[PDB]
Image: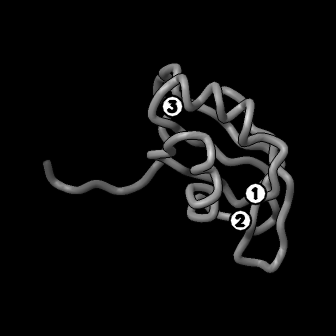
Amino acid sequence: GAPRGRYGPPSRRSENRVVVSGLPPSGSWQDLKDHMREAGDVCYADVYRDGTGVVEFVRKEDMTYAVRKLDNTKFRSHEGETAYIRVKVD
């Protein structure tokens, strides 16, 4: 009903969930969501400061395909730099 705030509590993981690893020193979930959209649909994106990011997709088919056709890519930042990242299932 009423709106909420944004947090990463320890919840379940359906068969539609992934993690992203090797993030640059200065990325965000915004560039994550806008990037990771090459593997189906990415209705959730979150990150930390850096090193990793944590993500949820729509379905297992897309999630599985992410590990096949959306890993070893480069990731863009707000900082003029771009790291490589390696996806995995959660």
x 13%, y 48%: residue: 1
Dot 3: element: loop
Please give the residue where the numbered disc 2 appears in the rendered image. 27
Label 1 Cα crowd, 10 Å radius (few <14 / some 14-19 / many 20+): some
- Identify the residue at the far bottom of this view: 80
Of the residues shown, which amino acid type is indicated by label 3? Pro
Describe residue 70's horizontal placement relative to residue 28 as left or right.
right
Q: What is the number of the mark on residue 62?
A: none
In 3D space, how far apart are the residues under numbered discs 1 and 2 (Cα atoms)? 7 Å
Q: What is the number of the mark on residue 10?
A: 3
Camera-near label (3 vs 1) is 1
Describe residue 5's horizontal placement relative to residue 29 as left or right.
left
Q: Position of residue 66 (x, y in %)?
A: 66, 35
Describe residue 28's horizontal placement relative to residue 14 as left or right.
right
In this rendering, the count of numbered labels is 3
In 3D space, how far apart are the residues under numbered discs 3 and 2 (Cα atoms)? 23 Å
Cβ atoms under marks 1 and 2 closer than 8 Å:
yes
Label 3 or label 2, whichever comes before in sequence order: 3
- Give whichever of 76, 24 is nearer the camera: 76
Label 3 or label 1, whichever comes before in sequence order: 3
Camera-near label (1 vs 2) is 2
x 81%, y 50%: residue: 73
Label 1 or label 2, whichever comes before in sequence order: 2
Please give the residue where the numbered disc 1 appears in the rendered image. 50
Res 62 quadrant in image: top right
- Specify the quadrant that holds the C terminus: top right
Dot 2: element: loop
x 75%, y 57%: residue: 50
Of the residues shown, which amino acid type is indicated by label 2? Gly
Q: Position of residue 87 (x, y in %)?
A: 74, 38
- Identify the residue at the far top of this view: 15
Of the residues shown, which amino acid type is indicated by label 1? Asp
